[PDB]
Length: 190
Length: 333
Image 1 (cartoon, each protein chain N blue to C red):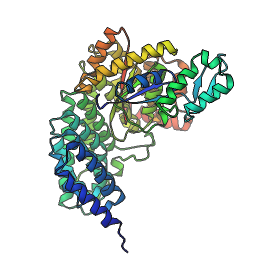
Image 2: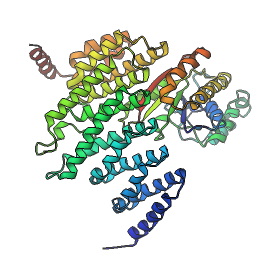
Image 3: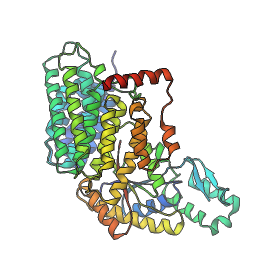
Image 4: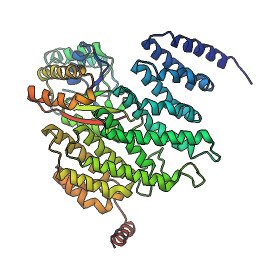
């Protein structure tokens, strides 16, 4: 709708960012998504499915298919991978992107810290500011869905503004009240 | 020795510059993107002849078009900085713009423009009249953006704070404790043979801009975005120029003790999280030696553990500490 470049960031770039990516893209937003982790982690507690960033969603689908096609259909991981492979080729790492945004949405405070640490670690060149917001999304299919609606609700309200910089703090303040949520908000520079 | 490349590129941009006068603002931005790529990239020689063609579009009614002109002028000072006196007027004029979106883009571009412009002007041994004109416009640009900290737009204020950060850093002297940054330029890099301006006068201005930022940072009705932006700009200044370390640590100490009552609960948490990060960064600087206990105090107030703070302090030899411990003792008397 608006000319806003939006990015949704999580740990793996699998469940929470992709649920929000999918809904924001369907609303017509210029959206990109990233993961803040070292590697892509998929669900024993001590036995996870680990992949490097840049590994195709299709290859991860056919890897967990050949591992156990029945188990990974019952836990909904193959259903998730089906959605992601339709959105883009592979999960991407935020720390490696050269893309610039107007708004960056993190799904948890731990991710927020990783995004802020990373952008602060780099010398600013363009002196271009970016709003970094945190919307707490619990890492499970049901909460990733509810969360994606909140993030879409928040980005839509912000897209309506004729001057986002001048209205953003009041918009967050009323959004927080209505939705009974805490939205951490920082400003970083490119 | 010659070839067809320049002529083939000139024919391509002549076509593009001709379409501009009769193109839609949307088509104008597409054309300008192509003109920039060729005239300042692929065939860099063609840049001076097609200047006025692009610079005239600074008057266009569409703000996107005006923003594209800014993007072009910013590239000119990066690759063909000798053209600086011919493009610098447009920048100053565009700071008088009605659209806040245009103002923000101009302030953003002025960061690299002022650094590249300052580097070029003090490099000339026999500077002409055009050089004195360009420096006069650059002086006015600094003053223009300095006024914008009292602008009614929050976005304008945020960009203005960021611009002023680079000026303070350029208009001060680096030292042993300064963070190693590749393209770092200080007053130490400004020659004595330079007639255009004096090192002492730029330092005086840099100190005045810092004093303004320090005061701005301590106001009671500052926005959360402006406060976070100002806190990080003060952190960059102190880590780049540790002479300012004491001043910045004091500003941070005063802020943590007196959070503006205009901040919301979320804004407080956001401001304190950023303050904690800035303090962690400063503690890593060798120049923060004198303020290590003050910084520790604040980090404990902001929830850091003893061991998290301890790991940040740089390892120093006793011969280095004695030099510092004695320099701190002689300066106090």
